Amino acid sequence: TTVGNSTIKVNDEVQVGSAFEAILGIEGLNGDTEVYSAEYLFEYNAEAFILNEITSFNDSLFVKSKEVEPGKVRILVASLGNEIEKDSDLVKVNLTPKISSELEVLGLTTALVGAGDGNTHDLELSSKEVKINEE
């Protein structure tokens, strides 16, 4: 089963040629789960978006990422010291749309946390739909 929820926060509407942020995080973690790292597989339609940069939501974490196939990005978030708070935002994914669309899905198809028991644990998955307006 799972120890908490993944979160993705993004505006409902984006626009061709205008950069926007998807914000990846966690929410509702079990009280006894002490989180030191997270891992997403972030998915998006590589025909519709340009991946610009993926960065930490703040400077108490570091992010590493690799687009392992077009539109599938492995994202490792790690604490620099402190326990990661239970409802924190962790990663900023900066994208620019390049085609209009009525509906595109930004998804987390893998979402895991490394904890103070030395083990990995599952999070519930998440996605968000956006409409891409014309430039």
Image: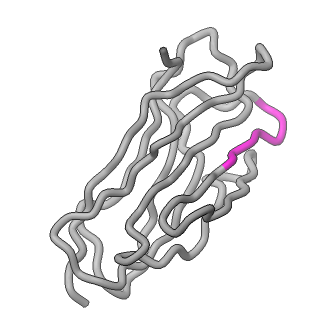
Q: Residue at x 46, y 43 (%)?
A: 109
Relative height, residue 126 to residue 19 (above, below):
above
Relative height, residue 17 to residue 75 (above, below):
below
Residue 9, percent from left and from top: 38, 50
Which residue is at the far right? Answer: 81
Asked if residue 113 lies left or right of residue 99, the reply is right
Residue 117, percent from left and from top: 77, 14
Q: Residue at x 55, y 37 (%)?
A: 88
| Tally of numbered tags | 0
Relative height, residue 121 to residue 125 (above, below):
above
Which residue is at the far top? Answer: 32
Residue 3, percent from left and from top: 53, 18
Q: Nearer the viewer, residue 40 or 84?
A: 40
Q: Residue at x 54, y 14 (%)?
A: 30
Asked if residue 7 lies left or right of residue 83, the reply is left
Residue 83, percent from left and from top: 73, 28
Instruction: Give the quarter of the image for residue 129.
Output: bottom left
Image quarter hosting the C terminus: bottom left
Asked if residue 105 lies left or right of residue 102, the reply is right
Instruction: Give the quarter of the image for residue 67.
Output: bottom right
* Image colouring: one colour
Which residue is at the far left? Answer: 102
Magenta span of residues: 76-82
Which residue is at the far front? Answer: 69
Q: Residue at x 65, y 37 (%)?
A: 38
| 86 magenta-colored | no
